[PDB]
Structures are given as structure tokens and as C-alpha cells.
Length: 201
Image (cartoon, one colour):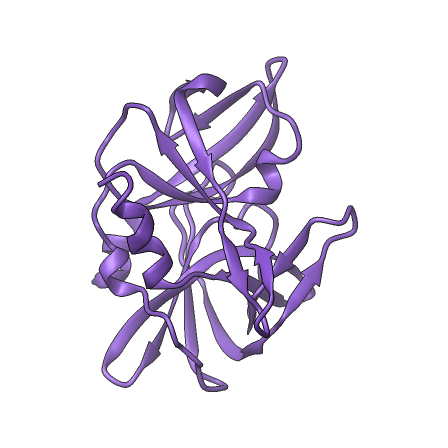
């Protein structure tokens, strides 16, 4: 039910260069024209980018990078924010995130995915614990992640992951990376999301 309203915001993303599909992932709308996106992809180069079929050029959107406090230290989240100069409205789902969430073990976990490989998919998983920092093979550091047990191929990055606490269904952040039957999300705080909605509305 809520799960679907998250999907309404999730959109297939891709990165092209010289005509060939170089990369592919997801992005989740949070408000207005703001989309949560895997930062470690805008690092490596792109020519064109497709969001939901829209043939975007480089100069038509702008990216916001955030820092996170991991053990009282300041690192740059792998969850970035792609904002279109002009585009379509997504729902405000920023109201669903939180800030001081410590999720219990074994709890269910859902991963709303929408891309060009699989399509509009959801998956299930189990909550493990908080991981401080995770480093990729090329050095794409991913701080403040959250570990959950589930099957996650490539192109799931950017999808929206939601769990439970009490009677509430909280969105934690966006799926970042994984493999080995385990997955990782860039933990995103509501406070952070609101302080940017102020600056864009």
C-alpha cells in the first residue's frame, strides 16, 4: 500500500556515453523534482543520462552531495541528490524518513526497485546491524551504511529500502551496493532531507 506510493517515486536510471548504455540503476523521488541517486556513478563519466525515458543532457539537472556523522566524524554519503532544472513532480515522501533510527535485528526489509533490467520490482530481506564504512574495489567509499540480508544484483542501487519500528514504516535511505546475499543502504536522515527541501521547495 505505502510500498506502492514509494514505487510511484522510483524511476529507471541509466548513464550513456557515445550511444552505448554504460551504466544502469534506480532513483527515488522524495519531493518536487529531487531524486535520491547513487553518487558513485556520477563520479565515473557520463555523456547523456536517461530518467524514466526522458533523454536528459548533462546541463539539465544538478547534484547535491551530503556529509554524514559516522562516530562523530564527517564523511560524504554515497546517496546524492539529482535535482532537475525543469521536470515532473514526485510525491513528498520525505515525511516518512526519520533521524535517530536504530533498527532491531531480524526484522523484515523491503527494497523497491525500478530499472531497465528487471523493471518495477520489490524484494524482501532481514535487518542485520549498522555498518560504519564500506570501501569499493576502486575506492568508492560508502559511509554510514546499513547491512541487511537479501539477494541484490547490480542495478538495484538507488532503490528505496523500508523497514518497521513500532507501528511505523520508515524509509531508511537508498540501496547502495552489495553482493554475497547481503545488501547495503546509505542511511539517510529526515532532518537532512528537510534542510534541502527548504533550499528548493
